[PDB]
Amino acid sequence: VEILNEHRGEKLNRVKMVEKEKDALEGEKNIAIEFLTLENEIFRKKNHVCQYYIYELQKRIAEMETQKEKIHEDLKLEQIDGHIAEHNSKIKYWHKEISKISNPIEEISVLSPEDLEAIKNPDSITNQIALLEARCHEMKPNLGAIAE
Amino acid sequence: VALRGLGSGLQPWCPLDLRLEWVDTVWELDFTETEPLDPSIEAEIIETGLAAFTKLYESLLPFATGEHGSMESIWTFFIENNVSHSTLVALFYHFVQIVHKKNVSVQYREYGLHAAGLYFLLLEVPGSVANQVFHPVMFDKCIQTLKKSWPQRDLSQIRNAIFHLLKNFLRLLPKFSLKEKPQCVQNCIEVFVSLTNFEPVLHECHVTQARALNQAKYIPELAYYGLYLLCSPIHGEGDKVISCVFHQMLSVILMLEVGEGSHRAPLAVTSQVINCRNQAVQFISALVDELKESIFPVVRILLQHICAKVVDKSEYRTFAA
Amino acid sequence: EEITPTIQKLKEERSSYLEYQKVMREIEHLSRLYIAYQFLLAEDTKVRSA
Amino acid sequence: KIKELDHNISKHKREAEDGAAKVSKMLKDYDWINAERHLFGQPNSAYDFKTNNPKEAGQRLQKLQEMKEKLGRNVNMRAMNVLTEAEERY
């Protein structure tokens, strides 16, 4: 029975005879999964920045509605030109339905006149898409971390 | 003789027992394999043979040149005559599938390679790509048949058909951009590497992007022409393509056979491969004059690979020196 | 018989990815159809505006 | 009045070119002059996609296919490497 038991101890050995290949593979795929969560967060920031672009457009829309309403209060065709450019910017407003993850798509941040423009912060334009490109180049994702 | 030439090419090539349903099934079989064609259609192809292929060539030459590359072109003439270009592509790919088998007679190999050349000529018409003609799997298979046309005066006919197909593909290559298809880079450069070892090339070749189709009658020279075409960033995108091609030539630079490792036997010392390595150095030097920037770190990485993988043979040491 | 389910799984992965690339090519050509129509609308807007 | 409308028309005409979001610059980029009229046969509609308001198509299906970022391309590479290992093991 002990000789039979020996091979059972050997069975306990070769269920995981080395374990380092699987640990390294699950470590690499865990790095991939953490890259997926981090790239999701940077992608959420990119959705926020595109939402800053839609709110820059819409805030500009509201301000020029105020100025064309002042023109109408005071000249008719100048108000009409303000209305035309406002409707052109509302036509360009289609990007408000940011289809990247739709969420930061309609959700605004706190500082609407200052933090909710994308053209005034090119670092937010550049560094986030650079981080997203570096991660999506270095993703190789798999649930083999969780599976292994 | 353009419309009448296209018609004259079309009577052997638009038969009475033409299966468009076979063409459609091969189209939805993802162009991986071809079932055997009809006896009638292949009988009408052979009833005149490669002369019918040259008749199709002079049928397509005014259309491919551009004086009939217009609205009055292949597509409208095919619409008014109820002709498909997809069935011609299927005939070409079945000839390719014939060439894929090893124990195949020489005339079938010539028919397949000239059929793929006529396919590339049909691809050469601008705006014909958008009309559902190009498919990547059959294109990769017809690229693979350049390697697979060896039998596994036959060889002169085989190399003439290979020469005509390579002329048509190298003519098609400046029009086409390899931006969306980096898989050919591995595939077609691998068939270039396999097709270097066909004939000894006596003279050192100065390789540019202006070598004519019939100027280089040697397959290593045409392969070097294709590689120098592929050095452009439109065709070679990023440094991954350059590293892949550098690892590709690394095998032939090392004076060794195809393969990797010490199990692979060293090549015999022959002056033909000395001439080939001098052509490789001249072509690499032509690549250096042009890049004068990117080539330096990539060839340093290739030199790191060279220092990693050495063979201690005094003749090999002299050649590498 | 242990690597054969792994072989079958990898064959499923490559066949699925081949279907995904066919989906990419098909809907890419579907977008290319309106890219052609967008060329037409561009030419129409230029000609109409001039 | 009509001169101000003509200024609007001229602004639209000059705004056709020189923009990726605009219409004539992408004509310049592609150089799709293999059709002078860029319709072929009959034009279907402007409903499957839209030029002025993009991202309204089966690009939702493109993105739904792009839910996964996993590179199953080497297994799908036509070197048939996993089935090459299968055939070598057989």
Image (cartoon, rainbow, N blue to C red):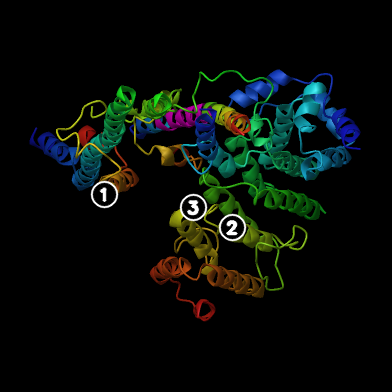
- The circle drawn on residue A123 is 1
Q: Position of residue A135 (x, y in %)?
A: 29, 45
Magenta-span inclusion, residue B188: no
Where in the figure is residue A133, as x and y percent of width and height?
33, 46
Residue at (91% x, 32% y) in the render? B4
Report the predominant secondary structure element of the magenta stretch: helix
Q: Which mark is residue B193?
A: 2
Please tell me how crowded label 3 is: few (under 14), some (14-19), or many (20+) other residues with Cα within 10 Å.
some
Q: Which residue position holds label 3? A: B237
**Residue that extends furthest to the left in the rendered view of this protein:** A2
Q: Is residue B207 above or below residue B193?
A: below
Closer to the eye: label 2 or 3: 3
Compared across the picture, whether B138 is left or right of D18 comes to right
Residue at 51% over, 35% down: D7
Q: Does the magenta segment cover residue C14?
A: yes
Q: Which chain is indicated by disc 1?
A: A
Which one is in front, B36 or A63?
Answer: A63
Q: CA distance from mark 3 to mark 1?
A: 27 Å
Q: Are the residues under marks 2 and 3 on the same chain? A: yes
Q: Nearer the viewer, mark 1 or mark 2?
A: 1
Q: Along the polypeptide, which appears first: circle 2 or circle 3? A: 2
Q: Position of residue B135 (x, y in %)?
A: 61, 34
| Residue kind at label 3, given as amino acid type | Glu
Rendered position, A43 above or below B219:
above
Tell me where the magenta segment starts and ends, as one range. C12-28
Q: Secondary structure at mark 1?
A: helix
Chain letter of the residue carrying label 3? B
- In the image as oriented, which residue stretches furthest toward the front? A74
